[PDB]
Length: 238
Length: 399
Image (cartoon, rainbow over the protein chains, first blue to last red):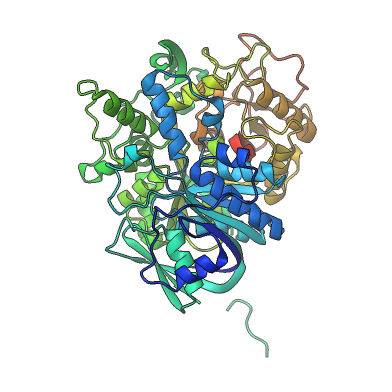
């Protein structure tokens, strides 16, 4: 079980970037993404910088920068299930084809390249962490954020993201697995505005990413909402 | 009205390890004292194009992945299973005592089953049949698979996640497990991690001009970069008193460069200072520092300057990466494990290897060991400085 306050947010997904788009979407059931809808451009990064980051990373760094411009934060946690899968796939293809690897592509393939690049671009020498936990990367990553609040970091920037899943992998992932890029940034603080308890579930491979299940339920404003994971669920209450 | 006034520290209970020094803690302890790593030698088929490469390998036959868990069948998870078998009675006792819900599983990795992902791409692209017998599953290559696999294997229902902060992954895992116990969310935590040899990091570090084809020489005149190794380490952290305490933890970010360190070591200094203040000790109370010491020009220069600044010239220190290799995501927990062995088995301190090119004469004096010597104070420090400028410092002590 965990309790926290969430005091600000910034998010981007196919067809969803403006506050009014997110609010309208939270009013709609079921919670769903059309992967054919366009993504908005990065607003805090020069286009050359944005286009050199991967499809998910650029959104995650942009959303993080938006919150760093509005708040003094003490620590940063990024979460991603698939991490830099596009770069990993490119490098595994370089190895298969006996082609040279780009040193920048390799350096940026580390899971923490998004949070690392954010600290460099924002000149922000803050404690940083980067978490992966399969389907439950978002929910388990909140425990990493809570360890940093426990250790005395008052305001923790928390960003969940994925890049596009290369078509190569579509035959080895579940038919339900989301394959589009998105990012959800939250500003976390010590408090009891929200509580979350974990339970067993019969569900797995949700069709909507956990951070977007969360944002839908949180923006919709009902007293109780559920985030589904890997044969578990996360019971949120206001 | 008056009421009767009668009406926490984290310890290490057990460590399981595999690395180039051996397949279990007994063999690793012996080989560390001898300064010989049987798994460290030149191997073909990794470094393109058609080159041999000195690598720190685990050659042990690994336990089979139970066939009901075949989605998790990576060498990475079989290395973790081999480490778990060394501490299984202690883990079984913790689960039975505290319950499934009050144990955490916090891993670190920079690879997961990356070699399995590499095999899958090459076998698919060229329709290869004969070379490969491996049943690939996407779960094997996910960075969250180490903690997911161990939680499923042990039925652990507490927090379960993997840190992936490059070379600091498995030392961050130790910090997070320590904090989840301090917070009261769990009573014990299985922490550590594993990284396994893959063509991707070997050729990636070569692309950065940061791979030594020959065995690395940390802090030496002729040093030409890193030697990659693989390792698994599991530590059982607990609130219940044990002979060894986790006295201090420290963390920082450089906010400087994605692969080069802060030239003034600002982040390294911040992490070391944070660990000393958590432990409530001065630099003078450290008996030994297990350095990061990767063998790159920039890392070893920065680190010698930082140790000279905080400790001066009289604190024994060395990098053991000439024995294990740089085990990447596994390095933090591997080196914490070696430090735990020095303390529990009263081993002599490992020297820096100056038998080949000799010390870099441009580096400040910082207490680098020219020969093995006894540990004079029962407190040791292990530091890790990673890509994305991600830094950790750990302090272990006799309770």
